[PDB]
């Protein structure tokens, strides 16, 4: 096909022949043959890295959406968040009114960071224990693609469509991981939110670009 | 002396027991230094060897490229806009521009965007040729030692001299990598170019050690 | 039967099965089956990682004790040091009086950082070479548990007690590594010594914390 097997699409296009590791045979989703460092030579380490990459991809997609949503709502809509910027959103818990969802005092209206931290650690501990072990939402199933309770719409029923959807998921997750790394670097250098950066760039693409005197005078703060 | 069981190991006389079993002194620069076991897997070993050699060659280029402008400006007579390596790039954001060797008739770069994109295209083509062959060859070598077109003088036509030159290359590249890390750390801590730091140290060595800016880690 | 074998104490408790890699069979001390990144799948890499972890653990225990002792002695004992704070303790070599041990002017009274560094490199290079290959104090029988001259009290003469003590050592060392990471992060964030942080937290805990 196009995403699996020897005739798939590789990570260097025409110049990939000879740079493809022998253990990357196009069996798993997102197999572009990019293992120049040889970190996934061991099959056990390979599947550990696949699990880590997929979890990172899903977390990064969720984080990209949740970082773009508030700042976009503040600038391009009448929403009035206390701190719409993603890297300054955690600081509202130290403010007078705390975290207000959508800016309304009547939603959540957090005041203590202690309850937030415990509740989160307890909930995520149970969730991750269930992910690695199984629980109320499934006992067996794959560690990366459980399905059943996590595939209610039944989109992953045809094996070919399942493989294509896995390719789409891993590619979108890698794109979101790249975007989240970009968010980190822009926050460190520019100090302003991704939506603000995008608006400034589309305003003056040649002037307000990344090659700036102050934006490049320091390496990672 | 550089290959085989009786070679020169990393810990010297205290090397017995510190040499991994998979480091049998077959490849260039095998001092038996692997304490983390990162190169135990032969495929990972080969990948790490390729990465090490590419880093070594890049660092040997980089040390000369970082020392030559500063040396020419300080000890010679050339008048570069920015002599130090860690502020050379900032010269692109100057009224005069990025003039080569201070001459406004040479290079006279004015646009960082064109520079970065032509560099990206050219280096993409070069690195694609490096790992998959191209106009200069079909990559006959191990992707580290092609030869044929990258060895025009024929200095590696004798296997013994080839092995000796590989040892010399890897040792020089490791030394250059060490010096390049030194350049990075000196730039971060002291904020001065390598030539300036070296000249200062030769003046009053006992007072200008690295134990002056020991505070403020990075 | 609790820290070794198949039915061990694992790093996830009841949610551990299906997350413990097959190459962690509980043969070595401190085997909670925590290898989620697959960094120790290769047995030789696993042995190298075990050696690195144990050396780090011992160094971290020593460092935790040696970072807590001066500040605790200054704050509670009364001994006046030049810089009792662990991350400020290096700088006193650059002071006028110098690095005087325990504040007393007749102890050590170091005046040269260069001499200190160039003696430490030699002494520790010799010590590390003896650790890897053996020397005056042994023949490097075991890279991690040489015994003999390094076990003068003879507390490792029983295999069961030896295994129990190895488990205790590795757990204490992991705890000390965690504490040293905490020390580093507190120094970077708060800028004050661990004893000062602990005293301030015990004074008013509900306000003096990491979220300030
Ligand atoms: C034929 C040309 C072709 C080339 C040259 C590449 C090259 C690349 N592809 Mg690619 N592809 C190509 C065709 C294709 N690709 C793909 C599908 C993919 C995918 C899915 C992915 C890639 C990725 C990559 C990158 C992996 C290596 C890397 O990270 O470099 C970067 C390393 C460098 C050293 C670049 C340095 C040059 C740069 C100008 C530096 C910038 C200079 C700064 C100003 C200095 C920084 C300052 C200081 C502080 C450091 C690389 C850019 C991966 C990627 O995007 O990772 C990032 C990836 O996931 N490719 C397809 C579809 C089948 C192609 C079809 O023809
Ligand atoms: C018998 C004595 C002998 C000893 C003890 C060593 C020891 C060493 N050799 Mg060596 N060699 C020796 C004989 C020989 N060597 C070599 C050929 C080589 C080579 C080719 C290489 C070595 C390297 C090394 C180093 C590898 C381990 C390391 O990185 O430690 C360093 C780790 C430490 C923890 C020591 C640091 C001490 C320092 C005082 C710490 C203090 C830090 C700061 C002051 C403050 C801290 C900073 C804070 C703020 C974060 C190590 C210094 C390698 C190297 O140079 O890598 C760097 C390397 O490539 N050796 C030959 C020729 C065959 C020898 C012949 O007898
Ligand atoms: C070999 C890798 C490479 C390294 C190590 C650096 C290192 C650096 N570049 Mg850089 N560059 C590199 C590739 C490239 N640079 C540039 C174009 C620039 C520019 C325009 C600037 C830098 C700057 C910097 C510095 C980042 C600011 C700082 O304080 O750092 C710690 C740092 C010394 C900045 C600087 O020099 O400010 C003092 C700066 O303005 N670089 C290009 C062309 C696109 C590269 C191509 O590969
Ligand atoms: C155990 C390793 C070791 C560590 C962790 C440190 C840590 C430090 N020393 Mg240091 N030293 C160490 C070994 C040695 N020092 C010295 C002699 C000195 C002097 C003279 C000075 C320091 C200073 C410092 C501090 C750097 C200033 C700073 O910005 O702090 C931020 C740094 C951290 C929070 C630690 C981050 C490092 C990382 C966690 C450890 C990784 C490196 C290790 C490998 C070695 C830092 C706390 C300076 C100081 O005290 O100023 C306030 C100073 O003047 N040290 C010697 C004798 C040669 C050592 C011998 O091994
Ligand atoms: C990884 C997922 C993730 C995480 C950790 C966060 C985290 C956060 N979001 Mg968020 N968000 C996400 C995804 C995520 N978001 C997505 C996918 C969307 C699109 C629907 C949003 C839309 C969104 C809005 C519109 C707002 C937040 C806000 C917040 C902050 C307050 C937390 C709160 O009240 O939630 C707990 C809420 C409930 C349980 C209900 C917090 C930093 C609020 C904020 O302060 O913005 C800065 C806010 O107003 N988020
Ligand atoms: C080829 C190796 C090499 C050489 C010749 C030098 C040479 C020099 N370094 Mg240097 N350095 C190196 C590697 C090297 N370095 C590396 C790898 C690092 C990273 C840890 C540093 C970090 C460093 C700092 C932070 C400073 C120097 C400084 C200096 C200068 C004064 C001497 C001194 O204090 O030494 C210091 C040497 C070390 C910290 C490590 C040397 C290890 C090899 C010893 C054998 C001198 C020109 C100082 C300077 O700017 O002079 C005014 C200074 O402040 N170096
Ligand atoms: C990894 C172990 C380690 C390391 C690297 C250090 C390092 C240091 N200690 Mg230390 N210490 C340690 C363990 C360690 N300690 C332990 C376990 C204890 C408890 C007994 C102490 C008790 C201690 C005291 C009481 C003092 C130091 C001091 C010092 C500093 C000067 C060293 C000196 O002159 O003594 C070398 C002297 C001899 C070898 C004799 C130096 C930063 C002195 C200082 O100024 O620190 C603020 C100081 O007064 N240490
Ligand atoms: C391939 C390969 C082969 C070679 O051989 C070796 C090799 C080169 C190494 C190797 C290549 C590997 C590569 C490239 C590695 C790159 C890894 C990267 C960049 C991973 C990025 C991860 C990004 C993540 C998870 C972001 C999560 C964000 C969240 C949390 O969900 C929030 O936003 C949460 C959030 C939200 C939503 C609102 C805010 O207000 C507050 C916060 C809490 C921040
Ligand atoms: C052995 C071993 C076994 C154990 O078991 C585990 C272990 C200990 C981990 C392991 C040991 C491994 C070790 C020691 C790792 C060390 C790796 C290091 C330090 C690599 C260093 C790389 C250095 C490089 C490429 C520098 C290039 C510079 C350039 C680019 O060409 C320019 O200067 C370019 C340039 C020039 C020329 C002019 C300037 O104006 C502008 C710029 C762009 C900067
Ligand atoms: C035996 C033998 C026999 C053969 O026959 C020939 C042979 C092979 C040649 C020969 C071999 C010899 C061998 C192997 C010996 C090994 C030598 C060693 C280990 C020397 C190490 C010296 C260590 C030094 C100076 C550390 C100083 C740190 C500074 C100062 O600058 C900081 O400020 C620290 C610092 C701070 C505080 C803030 C950070 O931000 C930045 C940094 C720099 C990290
Ligand atoms: C398990 C696992 C499985 C997965 O699959 C992948 C995985 C998650 C990655 C993996 C997990 C691994 C993990 C968690 C890694 C964590 C590593 C850490 C935090 C190690 C910490 C080490 C800290 C040390 C040595 C401290 C030494 C201190 C000294 C020196 O002795 C002094 O204080 C010396 C000193 C003293 C005493 C007085 C002061 O004044 C001056 C100084 C010099 C500072």
Image (cartoon, coloured by chain):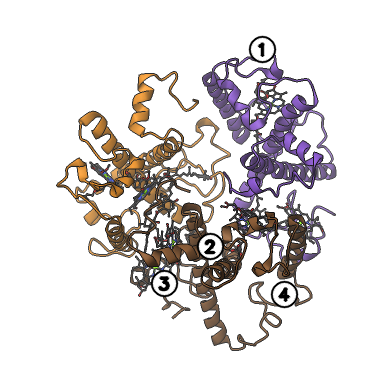
Chain colours: A purple, B brown, C orange
Q: Which residue corresponds to the image point at 69% horizontal and 21% vertical from the top-left?
A: A81
Rendered view: C49 above or below B84: above
Give percent across and percent down for residue A122: 55, 24
Any atom of ligand 5 within 8 Å of the CB at mark 1? no
Give percent across and percent down for residue B115: 74, 60
**For the residue labelled by badge 4, is the local secondary structure a helix, a strand or a loop?**
loop
The chain carrying label 2 is B
**Residue B212 - label:** none
The earlier-in-sequence mark between 2 and 3 is 3
Q: Are marks 2 and 3 in contact (CB under 8 Å)?
A: no
Residue holding disc 4: B139
Quadrant of res B209: bottom left
Distance from disc 2 to disc 3, alpha carbons, whole Å, reads 16 Å
Rendered view: A68 above or below C119: above
Any atom of ligand 1 within 8 Å of the CB at mark 4? no
Quadrant of ligand 11: it is top left
Q: Nearer the viewer, residue A161 or A93?
A: A93
The earlier-in-sequence mark between 2 and 4 is 2
Quadrant of res B93: bottom right
Distance from disc 3 to disc 4, alpha carbons, whole Å, reads 32 Å
Residue holding disc 1: A105
Give percent across and percent down for residue B40: 52, 62
The chain carrying label 3 is B
Task: Report whether B102 appears left or right of A195.
Answer: left
Any atom of ligand 9 within 8 Å of the CB at mark 2? yes
**For the residue labelled by badge 1, is the local secondary structure a helix, a strand or a loop?**
loop
């Amino acid at each position: 096909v196009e995403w699996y097997g020897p005739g798939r699409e590789l990570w260097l296009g025409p110049y990939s022949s000879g740079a493809v590791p022998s253990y990357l045979t196009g069996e798993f989703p997102g197999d572009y043959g990019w293992d120049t460092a040889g970190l996934s030579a061991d099959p056990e380490s390979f599947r550990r890295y696949r699990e880590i990459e997929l979890i990172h991809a899903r977390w990064a997609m969720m984080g990209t959406v949740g970082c773009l949503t508030p700042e976009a709502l503040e600038r391009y809509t009448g929403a009035t968040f206390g701190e719409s910027v993603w890297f300054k959103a955690g600081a509202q818990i130290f403010s007078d009114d705390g975290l207000n969802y959508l800016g309304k005092p009547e939603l959540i209206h957090a005041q203590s960071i202690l309850a937030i931290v415990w509740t989160q650690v307890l909930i995520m501990g149970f969730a991750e224990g269930y992910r690695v072990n199984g629980g109320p939402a499934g006992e067996g199933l794959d560690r990366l693609y459980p399905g059943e309770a996590f595939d209610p719409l039944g989109l992953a029923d045809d094996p070919e469509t399942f493989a294509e959807l896995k390719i789409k998921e891993i590619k979108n997750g890698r794109l979101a991981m790249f975007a989240m790394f970009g968010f980190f670097v822009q926050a460190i250098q520019t100090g302003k939110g991704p939506v603000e950066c995008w608006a400034e760039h589309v305003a003056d693409p040649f002037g307000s670009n990344g090659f700036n005197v102050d934006q490049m005078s320091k390496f990672l703060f | 002396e550089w290959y085989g069981p009786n070679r020169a190991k990393w810990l010297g006389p205290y090397s017995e027991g510190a040499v991994p079993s998979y480091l049998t002194g077959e490849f260039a620069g095998d001092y038996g230094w692997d304490t983390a076991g990162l190169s135990a897997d032969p495929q990972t070993f080969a990948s790490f060897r390729e990465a090490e050699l590419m880093h070594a060659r890049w660092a040997m280029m980089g040390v000369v490229g970082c020392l030559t402008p500063e040396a020419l400006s300080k000890y010679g007579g050339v008048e570069f806009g920015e002599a130090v390596w860690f502020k050379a790039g900032a010269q692109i954001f100057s009224e005069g521009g990025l003039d080569y060797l201070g001459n406004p008739t040479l290079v006279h770069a004015q646009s960082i965007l064109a520079i970065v994109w032509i560099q990206a295209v050219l280096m993409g083509l070069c690195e694609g040729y490096r790992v998959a062959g191209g106009p200069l060859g079909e990559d006959p070598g191990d992707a580290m030692y092609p030869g044929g077109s990258f060895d025009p003088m024929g200095m590696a036509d004798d296997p013994d001299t080839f092995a000796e030159l590989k040892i010399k290359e890897i040792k020089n590249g490791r030394l250059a990598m060490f010096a390049m890390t030194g350049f990075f750390v000196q730039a971060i801590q002291t904020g001065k170019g390598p030539v300036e730091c070296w000249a200062e140290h030769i003046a009053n060595p006992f007072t200008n050690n690295g134990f002056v800016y020991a505070t403020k880690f990075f | 039967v609790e820290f070794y074998g198949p039915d061990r104490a694992l790093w996830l408790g009841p949610y551990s099965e299906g997350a413990v890699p097959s190459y962690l069979t509980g043969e070595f001390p401190g085997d909670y089956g925590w290898d989620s990144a697959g960094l120790s799948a290769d047995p030789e890499t696993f042995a190298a990682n075990r050696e690195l972890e144990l050396i780090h653990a011992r160094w971290a225990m020593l460092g935790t004790v040696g970072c807590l002792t001066p500040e605790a002695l200054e704050k509670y004992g009364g001994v006046e040091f030049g810089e009792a704070v662990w991350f400020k303790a290096g700088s006193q070599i650059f002071a006028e009086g110098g690095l005087d041990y325990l504040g007393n002017p007749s102890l050590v009274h170091a005046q040269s950082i260069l001499a200190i560094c160039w003696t430490q490199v030699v002494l520790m290079g010799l010590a590390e070479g003896y650790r890897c290959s053996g020397g005056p104090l042994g023949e490097a029988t075991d890279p991690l548990y040489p015994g003999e001259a390094f076990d003068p009290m003879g507390m490792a003469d029983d295999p069961e007690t030896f295994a129990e003590l190895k488990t205790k050592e590795i757990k204490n060392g992991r705890l000390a590594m965690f504490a040293m990471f905490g020390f580093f992060v507190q120094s970077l964030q708060t800028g004050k010594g661990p004893v000062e942080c602990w005293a301030e937290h015990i004074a008013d805990p509900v306000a003096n914390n990491g979220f300030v």
